[PDB]
Image 1 (cartoon, rainbow, N blue to C red):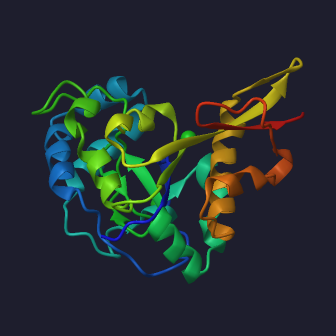
Image 2: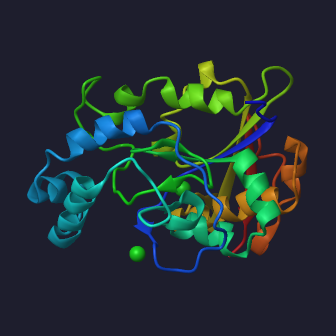
Amino acid sequence: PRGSHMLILISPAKTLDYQSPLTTTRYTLPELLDNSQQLIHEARKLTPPQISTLMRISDKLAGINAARFHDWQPDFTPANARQAILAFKGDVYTGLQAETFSEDDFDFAQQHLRMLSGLYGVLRPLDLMQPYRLEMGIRLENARGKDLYQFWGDIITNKLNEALAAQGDNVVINLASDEYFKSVKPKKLNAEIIKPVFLDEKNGKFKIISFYAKKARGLMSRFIIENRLTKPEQLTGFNSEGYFFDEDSSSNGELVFKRYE
Ligand SMILES: [Cl-]
Ligand SMILES: [Cl-]
């Protein structure tokens, strides 16, 4: 893989959509399914009551997810799976708004965007995925350890490095939640890390407000893709929905964007 000099990382989503019209029919296949299969083997051992307490979800949703683990099999097709960038729904994906992407937009995203995933490890935008719930921070015991950080080890970082240029200045734009970015090993990552941070106002102070911040990470992802950005300095132009760059508040690889109420 050639890789590129700019890679965006975002979180996955809990809500999945396999019924809306496909915005593109082009797809690829996830590259870490041998690992995924091992996790499915463990996940299948859980009863629905165990899923409900472990994942803190309703009995009904635990049942649905028990069935998903039972039903999962690695021969992915459009009849049984959907591209990750289309399947995921939630605040990040509302900001990203992939349903308005052109085929060229999808090609740029396929080169420059990756979703982290408890089950799949690393997803490309066009990678088909079968439905699941397995959040990265879940304490699922496995052959390699007591949780998914121990399971994935350096694998996720190594896969991201494959998508980065072998030499030259690379940047990884961390637009993922800490739960997911914890699966990446910065000392082993072949890139500078830049973390755009979105702060909203409250009582004269600026703070991370989760529902706003998730949508903002999506808006920024879309900004980068739509404008085909190549360099870190270009990210400071982001101003969607009232955010503005704050240079003085930005250090240590954070790029801070503030927004008034
Ligand atoms: Cl659905
Ligand atoms: Cl997020």
